[PDB]
Amino acid sequence: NAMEIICFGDSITRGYDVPYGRGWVEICDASIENVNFTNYGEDGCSVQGMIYNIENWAVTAVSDPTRHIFLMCGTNDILQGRDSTYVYKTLVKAIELASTKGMVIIGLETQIDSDMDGLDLVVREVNEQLKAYAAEHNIKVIDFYTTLFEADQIGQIVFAGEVHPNERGYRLMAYKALEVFTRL
Ligand code: NA
Image 1 (cartoon, rainbow, N blue to C red):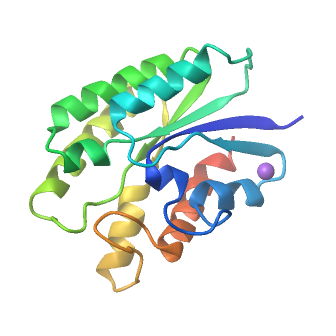
Image 2: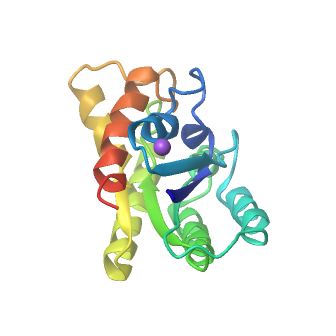
């Protein structure tokens, strides 16, 4: 049977605010036949709240030596004022926890488009440290941040607001995630 990929995160993993099927997770699920994606994303979620989601799943999870676990979070924490050290440290805890039940894939969260000279710098600092951690531990990374930054910079309409992708932004993210998921 299929591979299982379990996805955790906030509203940008859940797919706010487009029809079911058009968030990036769901695009990926419709694009790969023998990989089944389950979305545990939760709107409004903080990085510590995601840990709780992972724990509540992990205590019920069957052993599965081909499972992958996708994680991405921290935007809400950054919007509420937390610094890159807090966000990064808490994500590492999530990554260590998820690693006990599957092979982890890390997503680099997208830009804070309302504050490219303030809050977005925290996002960038988190993402640099994540790339360094993943290289050290041989964990796959999906760089969503770069995908949408480049597209928006050239004039593609990809954001519906200060952080949420629109449908175009979710398609571009799905393509970028598929570069990793397809090779598993
Ligand atoms: Na599928």
